Image: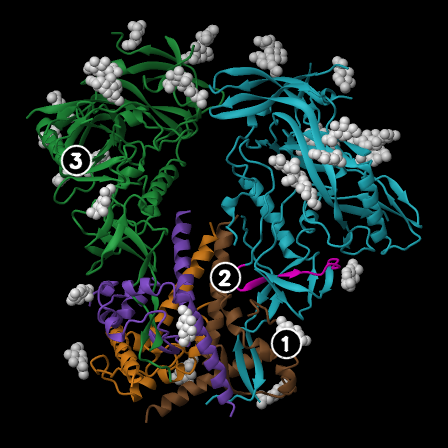
Chain colours: A brown, B orange, C purple, D green, E cyan
Amino acid sequence: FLGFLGAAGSTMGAASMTLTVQARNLLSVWGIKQLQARVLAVERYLRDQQLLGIWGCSGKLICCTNVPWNSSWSNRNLSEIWDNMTWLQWDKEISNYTQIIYGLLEESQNQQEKNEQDLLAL
Amino acid sequence: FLGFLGAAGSTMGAASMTLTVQARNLLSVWGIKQLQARVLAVERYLRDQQLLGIWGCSGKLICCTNVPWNSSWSNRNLSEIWDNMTWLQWDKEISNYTQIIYGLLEESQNQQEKNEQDLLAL
Amino acid sequence: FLGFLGAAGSTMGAASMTLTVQARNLLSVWGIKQLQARVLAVERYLRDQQLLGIWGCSGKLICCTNVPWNSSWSNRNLSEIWDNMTWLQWDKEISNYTQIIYGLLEESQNQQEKNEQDLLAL
Amino acid sequence: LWVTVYYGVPVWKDAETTLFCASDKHNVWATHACVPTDQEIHLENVTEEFNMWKNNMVEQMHTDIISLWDQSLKPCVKLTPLCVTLQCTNVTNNDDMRGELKNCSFNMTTELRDKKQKVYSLFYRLDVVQINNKEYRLINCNTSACTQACPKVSFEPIPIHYCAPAGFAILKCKDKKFNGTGPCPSVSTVQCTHGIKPVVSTQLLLNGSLAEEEVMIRSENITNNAKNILVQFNTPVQINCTRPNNNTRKSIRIGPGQAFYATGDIIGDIRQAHCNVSKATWNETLGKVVKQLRKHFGNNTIIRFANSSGGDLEVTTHSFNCGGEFFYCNTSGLFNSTWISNDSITLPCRIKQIINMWQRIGQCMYAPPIQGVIRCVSNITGLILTRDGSTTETFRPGGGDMRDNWRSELYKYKVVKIEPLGVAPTRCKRR
Amino acid sequence: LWVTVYYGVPVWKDAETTLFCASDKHNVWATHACVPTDQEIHLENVTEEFNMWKNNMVEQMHTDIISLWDQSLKPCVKLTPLCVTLQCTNVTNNDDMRGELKNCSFNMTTELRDKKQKVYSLFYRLDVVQINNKEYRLINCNTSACTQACPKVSFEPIPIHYCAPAGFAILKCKDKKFNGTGPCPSVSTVQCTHGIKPVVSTQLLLNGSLAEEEVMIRSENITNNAKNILVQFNTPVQINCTRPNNNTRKSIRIGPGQAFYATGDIIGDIRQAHCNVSKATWNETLGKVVKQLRKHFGNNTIIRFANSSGGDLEVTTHSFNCGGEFFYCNTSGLFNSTWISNDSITLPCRIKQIINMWQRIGQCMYAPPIQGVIRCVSNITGLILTRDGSTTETFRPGGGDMRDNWRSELYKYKVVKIEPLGVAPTRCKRR
Ligand SMILES: *[C@@H]1O[C@H](CO)[C@@H](O[C@@H]2O[C@H](CO)[C@@H](O)[C@H](O)[C@H]2NC(C)=O)[C@H](O)[C@H]1NC(C)=O
Ligand SMILES: *[C@@H]1O[C@H](CO)[C@@H](O[C@@H]2O[C@H](CO)[C@@H](O)[C@H](O)[C@H]2NC(C)=O)[C@H](O)[C@H]1NC(C)=O
Ligand SMILES: *[C@@H]1O[C@H](CO)[C@@H](O[C@@H]2O[C@H](CO)[C@@H](O)[C@H](O)[C@H]2NC(C)=O)[C@H](O)[C@H]1NC(C)=O
Ligand SMILES: *[C@@H]1O[C@H](CO)[C@@H](O[C@@H]2O[C@H](CO)[C@@H](O)[C@H](O)[C@H]2NC(C)=O)[C@H](O)[C@H]1NC(C)=O
Ligand SMILES: *[C@@H]1O[C@H](CO)[C@@H](O[C@@H]2O[C@H](CO)[C@@H](O)[C@H](O)[C@H]2NC(C)=O)[C@H](O)[C@H]1NC(C)=O
Ligand SMILES: *[C@@H]1O[C@H](CO)[C@@H](O[C@@H]2O[C@H](CO)[C@@H](O)[C@H](O)[C@H]2NC(C)=O)[C@H](O)[C@H]1NC(C)=O
Ligand SMILES: *[C@@H]1O[C@H](CO)[C@@H](O[C@@H]2O[C@H](CO)[C@@H](O)[C@H](O)[C@H]2NC(C)=O)[C@H](O)[C@H]1NC(C)=O
Ligand SMILES: *[C@@H]1O[C@H](CO)[C@@H](O[C@@H]2O[C@H](CO)[C@@H](O)[C@H](O)[C@H]2NC(C)=O)[C@H](O)[C@H]1NC(C)=O
Ligand SMILES: *[C@@H]1O[C@H](CO)[C@@H](O)[C@H](O)[C@H]1NC(C)=O
Ligand SMILES: *[C@@H]1O[C@H](CO)[C@@H](O)[C@H](O)[C@H]1NC(C)=O
Ligand SMILES: *[C@@H]1O[C@H](CO)[C@@H](O)[C@H](O)[C@H]1NC(C)=O
Ligand SMILES: *[C@@H]1O[C@H](CO)[C@@H](O)[C@H](O)[C@H]1NC(C)=O
Ligand SMILES: *[C@@H]1O[C@H](CO)[C@@H](O)[C@H](O)[C@H]1NC(C)=O
Ligand SMILES: *[C@@H]1O[C@H](CO)[C@@H](O)[C@H](O)[C@H]1NC(C)=O
Ligand SMILES: *[C@@H]1O[C@H](CO)[C@@H](O)[C@H](O)[C@H]1NC(C)=O
Ligand SMILES: *[C@@H]1O[C@H](CO)[C@@H](O)[C@H](O)[C@H]1NC(C)=O
Ligand SMILES: *[C@@H]1O[C@H](CO)[C@@H](O)[C@H](O)[C@H]1NC(C)=O
Ligand SMILES: *[C@@H]1O[C@H](CO)[C@@H](O)[C@H](O)[C@H]1NC(C)=O
Ligand SMILES: *[C@@H]1O[C@H](CO)[C@@H](O)[C@H](O)[C@H]1NC(C)=O
Ligand SMILES: *[C@@H]1O[C@H](CO)[C@@H](O)[C@H](O)[C@H]1NC(C)=O
Ligand SMILES: *[C@@H]1O[C@H](CO)[C@@H](O)[C@H](O)[C@H]1NC(C)=O
Ligand SMILES: *[C@@H]1O[C@H](CO)[C@@H](O)[C@H](O)[C@H]1NC(C)=O
Ligand SMILES: *[C@@H]1O[C@H](CO)[C@@H](O)[C@H](O)[C@H]1NC(C)=O
Ligand SMILES: *[C@@H]1O[C@H](CO)[C@@H](O)[C@H](O)[C@H]1NC(C)=O
Ligand SMILES: *[C@@H]1O[C@H](CO)[C@@H](O)[C@H](O)[C@H]1NC(C)=O
Ligand SMILES: *[C@@H]1O[C@H](CO)[C@@H](O)[C@H](O)[C@H]1NC(C)=O
């Protein structure tokens, strides 16, 4: 056990076994200021959980999806990503490709929603 | 792309392909006004997410359920519902039966929650 | 229909028929007193949904896990728990074993998260 | 056996939280700081432990009744100019109401800053303190300035329901022999409480809720004489007030837009203000109280009711509000009896206009005169007794702490926190 | 390769947010506007970039320390009646404390509006301005009215912890050579900061946190002479205050419930208020400062310490609070030396009662007299220097901006926003 953000400097493979530690800490003059800090924490948490549900990843911490990895985003191989890079370094590399990936996941699930809707119709 | 509420005049079949657009827009003296509106937006969002959870539809935008359609709620066939009406016209038609269906979906899931629960005990 | 907390005195078997009754009632300077109570209910509800999500139980009122029931927590047989005890009596008996169970459920899910993630790449 | 997680189990823990008001001419405890109302579910086989003496609804209601009191007094007149020197003479110069009054003349500010105003008013002797037609001054003038009780807000208590937020429930004890503590066999989950009128009074619980079958004695520790005894009647004892005088309210413009309402003249029936309690009804009510009070001290003990020991006028008298004017009744003929194993009782009441209500110093209030004759019909639904520290037990009336008044209405209620996430063994196994 | 979504990745961005107070007799920065406290996690291989000069915690703490100051002054006396004409005579009519005082007599309001009160008080010459026994008036009377420093609230700073809300983290730089900017090899995630005492002072960082290994020089741009230099000591320099006089506080009732506390008499040791700094300890501390200060300007340069240039008394003097009474010490013997490649220093301090603390106009405060002798023990844990725009560099003391005082405590902390949603390639494929 490392603690909150303990694996920030750890490799992506090693830091992915402690996702629960960071996940559980995202939810919980000194009056309204302290009260609006709690409402901001809930709204920030709820819009992240909404994104997971839209991508079909609701209730999951590691969600393998159907969107293929465009090599333009990152040409590195798996060995030097999950064993040589940390999540802070990785976020810097793909910070500009984040929004195009988000749209790809959003539409891919929307296609899967109608694909399973038609399969159940038979 | 049409935008938020853009498919309001589109037929029910065409407007059901843009659910992610409306879903992501439901979450985001004079200081409580801003703050109390935010808390009410979070509360309303959680009420609709709770309903989907107790119907077995959590994390889904299109959720095919086990509740049969009585035809006393609407006698129209699928051709004239998903290709002629819009979601606003449809909403004004089954508004009377909304709480009848909302009770059947909850009851069906609860029975289905235990039939699957009793199946794992074998 | 017994109502909210109606099955509080019923046996654990009969009280489990009505989990949705209590579930839907957990969510819904004088303005701040009301406003701060609303925020407390939201973040109290979300912490329980987050716990279910990290155990692989999100969106389910009854969730089956892969954690075997250590007899140290309670050695009473299945017949004298679901037909003789009420939920209030049960909570007082396993109150001190609650946190160790919570850690086991969290450790059981992320083990299944990685095992399914590994098996899905084959 | 495997762990299975149930969400929504009917499990609750004791909790302290902020309950919001609900209610169904502005008021002190107005509906503008409350919510419209709309219910009760019987929880069978549930035996919960209540404690009316460590209940946080009582402590919160005390804060809220105070808070709505101050919030209703800020927007109206502050009587800083009323600290002038008063040249007061007697009204009668000779048993009547007029022997309680001083005819006080003073210079008052006008709506124009540079002009004065020689005015007079009839002040009760309880509100003026002599300075050494003598020279007097208002009593709460070296401690604070008296914000005038605003004439358009009423002191009449309206019922308020304290309703629990989401995730909490209010447990109501339906047991009819429930004293204040221990298990309660019959429990219910109410959305929120019955209408609790915040009647402010001492030594007597005016109006409110009666007992169901017999007079109930409720003390935190009946063997401790430092703890008040909250008696609750089963049949109310009706008490009738009056101020027979036909008062004449007079308006003085002490500034731009600010008016000071003064007693200009007093005519009519000049008998002292009094309350009437039926002598037969009160005697049989003390008989019921004594019968239920020998159960805690013995059958052969001597139950004696004496009158209040001493202290402030707010604690030695049945202080209350009736018709917008504040009374302070003696209640020494009510509590005067020794009990061994058409007629009426008249309680002489004084009246004050400068009120330090919530046992505080530095925040007074000037209750303006009420035009006309004041008449009053209330139910004595309880008592607050103190015991004296021998075969004779003496029970003097008590009070002072306003929380014991609302502790008598919130004794049956309890706030719990729902714990909907519970784990239990089952033959399940996740696939 | 396929996109796989990871929720909960340890990724953070820089953010500005509202950190809430936490703390472990009412205070100016009281615990009624804070939260009880309860922690530190070492983040290995993490090298974060800090910037103590564009840190928003410093800007927020300045707002909050001000906000708690005003919030603590509203409920107590406003001295509007103290703007009368004062007939002031000398106290000594001849080096002492009594040469700093004027014996001022004035008409004051009584608790009765129509009566006056011929009273007197000893006012410092720094608080009275002559009108042309001469005629004087209080200094902040054409700009505002002085809300009296409420006598039951203490000015003693209690440690406050600024704690980040959910979704945010506070990064703490554990590097011992970290000046104020650039990468920090050793970082930690604290739940929230160490107890930061809001000590308000100028030219000298009284109390607070020491450096770890050597005196630290911290400037936003060391080559820019318009930027203050925040020196931080490794060993504290103890400074002892005093006001030797035995003051006699006197109470004046200026209205109903309002009292004005005045200096009625002064007896005892009448030596001027002063602070003592050990001459040996201060000389070796400036030696350490000079050694660490030649690293930025050259080994052969001449480091000269001069005294404050000019301006307000709050900026030319070591302004601070000690024992509830506000001192203004010269510190011209502290900063007087030229450095080439048992004894004590006594700093004469003046005292004021009318305080415009946060470099503002229109909100003064009257600090009431403190009964008795005032004694003081503080640690000089830092400096605030300004450089003069040649082989000689002259470093005058600086200050004025209160943010540089708390910038010296929040230099090691940083607030980040957790970004828990990250995507990465993996051999997965959704089934
Ligand atoms: C109202 O004010 C008047 C003055 O404006 C007061 O009359 C004065 O009383 C003093 C004695 O205290 C005399 O010495 C003056 O000669 C009086 N002035 C007159 C009569 O013009 C009067 O007493 C005040 N009334 C009160 C305080 O009730
Ligand atoms: C304000 O004035 C009243 C009246 O003079 C003070 O109360 C009196 O106190 C003395 C001294 O204990 C008693 O002998 C009197 O009987 C008291 N009078 C009444 C009517 O109670 C009171 O103490 C003063 N308050 C302050 C804060 O000075
Ligand atoms: C107890 O309750 C009675 C009944 O509500 C109160 O008497 C009423 O007072 C209002 C306002 O003064 C009048 O408009 C009603 O006509 C009164 N009713 C009767 C039957 O007289 C009484 O004031 C309450 N006692 C208190 C508040 O001490
Ligand atoms: C309250 O009633 C009592 C009793 O009537 C009054 O006080 C006593 O009265 C009896 C005779 O009526 C006297 O023998 C006592 O000496 C009285 N005790 C006193 C005056 O202390 C009392 O005056 C009434 N009013 C108050 C305010 O107590
Ligand atoms: C306090 O007020 C008195 C008057 O109430 C002042 O005395 C007056 O002073 C003026 C000169 O400015 C004379 O012309 C008057 O004759 C005086 N009146 C008297 C003595 O009754 C006195 O100067 C004031 N004290 C102050 C301002 O400190
Ligand atoms: C309030 O009065 C003070 C004192 O007269 C004013 O400060 C003086 O300003 C003049 C003109 O610049 C200087 O010569 C004096 O040396 C100042 N005196 C002090 C003690 O600083 C001040 O300017 C006035 N404020 C306002 C807003 O009018
Ligand atoms: C620096 O810290 C010291 C120690 O806390 C402060 O001195 C204390 O002040 C309080 C309140 O005046 C006294 O009760 C303590 O007895 C003092 N301690 C000692 C050792 O003298 C000092 O005031 C602080 N310096 C400031 C705030 O400028
Ligand atoms: C602060 O100390 C300085 C230095 O002691 C004082 O000012 C100078 O003092 C020297 C000799 O002590 C004189 O030669 C200078 O002419 C003084 N300069 C002045 C008076 O401007 C100073 O008086 C002390 N106090 C303040 C408030 O500056
Ligand atoms: C830091 O890196 C070392 C190896 O370079 C590794 O052993 C260690 O686990 C890393 N730190 C953390 C917190 O994982
Ligand atoms: C991959 O990204 C490039 C831009 O970086 C884009 O032009 C291309 O269309 C993308 N390919 C796919 C299959 O999305
Ligand atoms: C409106 O109706 C027309 C045909 O009637 C359709 O082509 C169009 O898409 C509709 N508008 C929207 C926004 O879908
Ligand atoms: C349809 O609803 C009616 C009542 O409106 C009910 O009587 C009927 O049984 C329902 N149909 C079915 C198939 O259950
Ligand atoms: C209380 O217990 C009885 C039997 O002991 C049972 O029939 C009843 O249903 C229980 N109450 C509730 C609310 O279930
Ligand atoms: C059950 O819990 C006890 C601790 O009370 C522990 O010693 C035992 O090993 C546990 N049984 C298991 C893990 O099978
Ligand atoms: C005024 O009344 C008091 C009490 O009633 C009395 O003591 C006093 O003598 C009276 N003053 C007169 C008659 O002048
Ligand atoms: C109140 O009643 C309960 C249950 O009968 C009893 O245990 C308790 O002792 C009573 N209260 C007192 C103060 O005796
Ligand atoms: C009280 O009773 C007396 C006679 O005993 C009567 O004169 C008076 O009017 C009554 N007052 C009230 C308010 O009933
Ligand atoms: C009180 O007054 C009512 C009428 O208002 C009358 O019927 C009743 O008899 C009176 N009771 C007493 C005790 O004065
Ligand atoms: C209680 O009654 C006695 C006489 O019986 C009296 O002297 C005393 O003042 C009374 N106390 C009160 C009414 O508080
Ligand atoms: C007193 O209570 C009775 C019923 O017990 C009620 O009819 C009457 O109106 C009440 N009087 C009041 C509240 O003044
Ligand atoms: C009062 O003191 C000042 C400064 O100390 C002096 O200039 C003045 O002459 C003194 N007034 C006298 C002695 O009357
Ligand atoms: C502070 O230290 C960092 C790292 O050594 C350095 O890059 C930076 O220039 C220093 N600050 C200044 C103002 O030079
Ligand atoms: C400062 O030192 C002087 C002598 O140098 C001494 O008289 C005085 O008491 C000292 N004051 C303090 C506060 O140490
Ligand atoms: C300050 O005072 C302390 C005792 O309070 C004393 O031990 C110390 O030597 C003094 N130091 C200076 C520099 O005056
Ligand atoms: C600095 O010292 C000089 C003399 O050395 C003095 O004239 C000047 O007033 C001082 N400035 C201050 C203390 O601000
Ligand atoms: C000064 O710091 C020392 C330790 O460096 C400490 O023992 C002493 O109490 C401090 N003096 C204060 C805070 O007055």
Tell me whether the residue at label 2 lies in contact with that at label 1, contact meaning CB atoms closer than 8 angstroms: no
In magenta stretch: residue E178? yes
Relative height, residue D167 to residue B118 (above, below): above
Residue E362 seen in render: no
Mark positioned earlier in the residue sequence (2 or 1): 2
Same chain assignment for discs 1 and 3: no
Q: Which residue bears the numbered disc 1?
A: A86
Task: Tell me which amino acid carries mark 3.
Answer: Leu
Count of numbered marks:
3
Q: Which residue bears the numbered disc 2?
A: A40
**Horizontal and vertical percent position of residue A91:** 62, 75
**Range of the magenta residues?**
E165-180
Q: Residue at horizontal 27%, vertical 7%?
A: D93
Residue D203 horizontal side relative to residue E279, left or right:
left
Task: Tell me which amino acid carries mark 2.
Answer: Leu
Q: Is mark 3 within 8 Å of ligand 16?
A: no
The tag on residue D293 is 3
Mark 3, Cα crowd under 10 Å, few <14 / some 14-19 / many 20+, is some
Q: How far apart are marks 2 and 1 (CA)?
A: 28 Å
**Magenta residues, dominant SS class:** loop
**Horizontal and vertical percent position of residue D164:** 32, 54
Mark 1, Cα crowd under 10 Å, few <14 / some 14-19 / many 20+, is many
The tag on residue C93 is none
Q: How far apart are marks 3 and 2 (CA)?
A: 57 Å
- The chain letter for the residue carrying disc 2 is A
**Horizontal and vertical percent position of residue B60:** 40, 79
